[PDB]
Image (cartoon, rainbow over all chains, first blue to last red; front, side, top):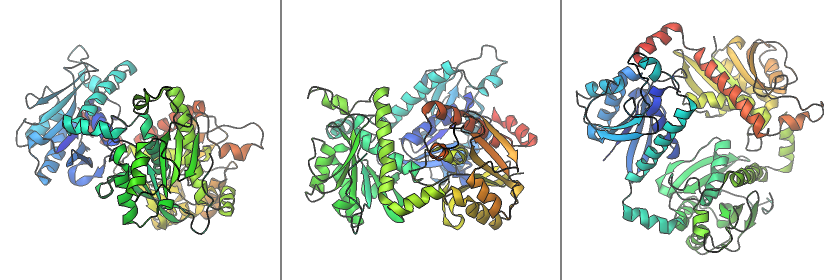
Length: 190
Length: 201
Length: 190
């Protein structure tokens, strides 16, 4: 069960469009579709919101700490509400998967992503939280990497990431009902 | 866009309900036409709907001709719309003839919208439930947003629960705009309105 | 330096979509991107919000006074916070520039726009505040003008105004971060 969903990013018009904000992209989609857009909450070093999913509180966060210090916010908020690492879902860009693919995982490696690195550290050195890996691709040589994650993707790629993010978001909504509630409802929908 | 009763002593609207089904699943479909409308109003009036479990939907408060008007979109699912409408209306002691209920309409085509007081539920289950749950009283205002007919009485469910093509959407959005611009005028009086346009330049 | 940004418009569902609200369109975009949408504040006769730009308070206002009396609100607020005219930025529709163009200026003529007229007057007769001129175009003859500004533009034009507004808002926000905060961020941004 999930009590907090964190979308990793760097704040600012400067970065808003870049590949590193993929996580935010996802949480902002969720947020908008669930009708509670993230507003500033300095107490947790990001922008936050509260929704209700399957009749329980789920909280959304996008840290305004900058990728490096994501940990700070994630830690802050999770302790305030006494949420365990395995109840946290962290959405991030992923160089290992391609545009148009997204995947879930519990724990495991930080795969070179500094936002994750810090979250492991600041969560008392515990990598056992859920990740949503939003595929962005590899630039080819290990050199062009920083410019690549801190770069805006071409329309063709954006088209593909948006689709993966949509589907991921769609699935998220659906976690919170069981097949028998989900059929109880189609008979009410019409 | 035509057909509200003219304003007066009472006559007057305290609650606007935009009928729909909740979920990304249905957000886009023809049945959410009502919500589409209320959301447009809400956004233009700068008070987007936020969750309020007390009334089983999303709600917001706006100010129109200096009077509280409240907006509701039920998260109950079309079938049980009544539950929410009823809940809210009793809490605020609002009468049926002060409720305006916006819905998709198979009788009118994309691009047309019309107002009505009372009368038939025209097969729409959302309305059916509201009449029932309001102590069996169909005397509330409706905004009929035209969506069209799929032809045969069979493909109907898929049609209302379907997303419309861009050509149709374009047309529904225009009607909804106009309606939302319209409702606005209905609350205003003839003299303040004109005087406002005068200052609006 | 800028302490208050005003986006000129008329309130109501009636006008929300019209060419006169171009100012509001801009401030609302800023506001939304900065995650502090404008809420009602009767004290200043409009909707207002507070953001933080380059670590200083910037305030956003969209007067609910109606174009004609825009001054009233601009004046009220600016005095409450002791803001000078050259620290006010005022975004308005411009019949001199076309759709898809936007431009900044300090002071100068009111160019027929009544909203600016009243602001000059109500600011103790002082035209020395900054303007963002969002281009909306000319209807041709000096007659159809009122219907034109109080009209909704066709999609083709809207598409173009939104692009200019976006750009303006991207620039506006970024002209606020200094090089030392900019540089300090990239350090953390990857």
